[PDB]
């Protein structure tokens, strides 16, 4: 693994994210000024829990598709056996979307971009899961505080997806190699960008999995399947 090869991987992954971002940071940042009216907020609050969950799930599944395209554009993912592909995606897909949310969250007004405007926790009152919603906002707040580069998100999301420790992997060694190469790339780019600091400040592995486990649990309580099981992708 030559420096030049490693630099190539950094470029590949960062470009892949740029293509599969799903939204433009520029656009999100400009839209921060546009905020939901109190009347609009009360409207969302008035909606039935069932309607909101369907609406939310539509957005989530949309995002997961983009994440899957990101995974396909990652080097070596395609080479892995279907079983190993699905395992990595199953475990990581939702985890990646939670990371990508940090872009949408605005720390000043504590609002997130939902259906074309910025809104606070108040919007999702209908769901009646205040603790889950608060935790997602808190998680996003921390990442927003870090002022994550698009290039940093790209490498981090990739590392989330590509983990040898995920159970059910037959080709563990192959995934390990891919993980280590992406690990090197992340460290290398942080050295180059003088952002070595952020490693310590990153959320622990445990916390990412915790929020995703409970998120899937709530969807399963409603008449829904795991998004990888309900995959229009892998057709």
Image: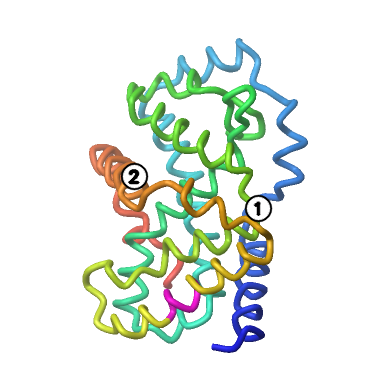
Q: Identify the residue at horizontal 52%, vertical 33% (top origin).
A: 141
Q: Which residue is mark 1?
A: 149
Q: Is residue 37 left or right of residue 174?
A: right
Q: Position of residue 133 (x, y in %)?
A: 40, 29
Q: Identify the residue at horizontal 53%, vertical 42% (top origin).
A: 143
Picture quadrant where residue 120 is located: top right
Using the image as rendered, state which of residue 210 and residue 68 is in the foreground.
210
> Start and end of the magenta stretch?
178-182
Q: Is residue 181 magenta?
A: yes
Question: What is the spatial separation of the Cα atoms under label 1 and label 2, in whole angstroms?
Answer: 21 Å
**Mark 2 packing: few (<14 Cα in 10 Å), some, or many (20+)?**
few
Which label's residue is closer to the chain start, 1 or 2? 1
| Whether residue 74 is situated above or below residue 80 in the rendered picture | above
Q: How many marks?
A: 2
Q: Is residue 39 magenta?
A: no
| Circle 1: element type | loop
Q: Is residue 167 left or right of residue 180?
A: left
Q: Which residue is mark 2?
A: 207
Using the image as rendered, state which of residue 51 and residue 186 is in the foreground.
186
Q: Identify the residue at horizontal 75%, vertical 43% (top origin).
A: 27
Q: Is residue 4 left or right of residue 155?
A: right
């Amino acid at each position: 693994a030559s420096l030049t090869e490693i630099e190539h991987l950094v470029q590949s992954v960062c470009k892949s994210y740029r293509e599969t971002c799903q939204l433009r940071l520029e656009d999100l940042l400009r839209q921060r000024s546009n905020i939901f009216s109190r009347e609009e907020v009360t409207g969302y609050q008035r909606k039935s829990m069932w309607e909101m969950w369907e609406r939310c799930a539509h957005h989530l599944t949309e995002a997961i598709q983009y994440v899957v395209e990101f995974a396909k554009r990652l080097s070596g993912f395609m080479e892995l056996c279907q079983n190993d592909q699905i395992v990595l995606l199953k475990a990581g897909a939702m985890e990646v979307v939670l990371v990508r949310m940090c872009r949408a969250y605005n720390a000043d007004n504590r609002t997130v971009f939902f259906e074309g405007k910025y809104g606070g926790m108040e919007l999702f009152r209908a769901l009646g899961c205040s603790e889950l919603i608060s935790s997602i906002f808190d998680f996003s707040h921390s990442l927003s505080a870090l002022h994550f580069s698009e290039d940093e998100i790209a490498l981090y999301t990739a590392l989330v997806l590509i983990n040898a420790h995920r159970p059910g992997l037959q080709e563990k060694r192959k995934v390990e190699q891919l993980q280590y190469n992406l690990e090197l790339a992340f460290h290398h780019h942080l050295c180059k960008t003088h952002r070595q600091s952020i490693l310590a400040k990153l959320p622990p592995k445990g916390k990412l999995r915790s929020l995703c486990s409970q998120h899937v649990e709530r969807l399963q309580i409603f008449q829904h399947l795991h998004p990888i099981v309900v995959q229009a992708a892998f057709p």
